[PDB]
Length: 130
Image (cartoon, rainbow, N blue to C red):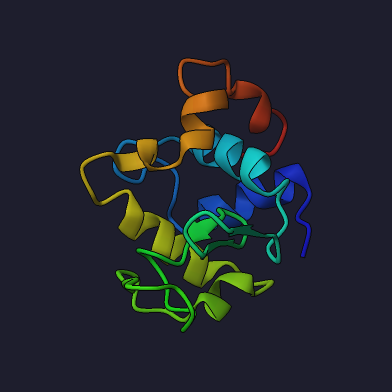
């Protein structure tokens, strides 16, 4: 599913993301906009280390979800990577919250650092009623 900007913002707010671990909704939005363009079936294969990024947040198979094919990977979210390709994003959000429960927090994603950190992200939630 390819969510519309404001549609993503309310779905994320409803799922308890606004301010989760000090991370604002605009920050989560900027991340999903750059990670997948708000597309839940987005995927990126990393031939360099044979892992795959899944869903709206492009979560990686090496640490967060089990896809059966990543060498010496773990499943810290205790979910099959299939759960991260659903139109319903509850499972992906649960996994993303788990990710930010570690030291780096939202810094976990290099895209966020690249185009969300120290940036004007208000534009992402402007007019969405959140």
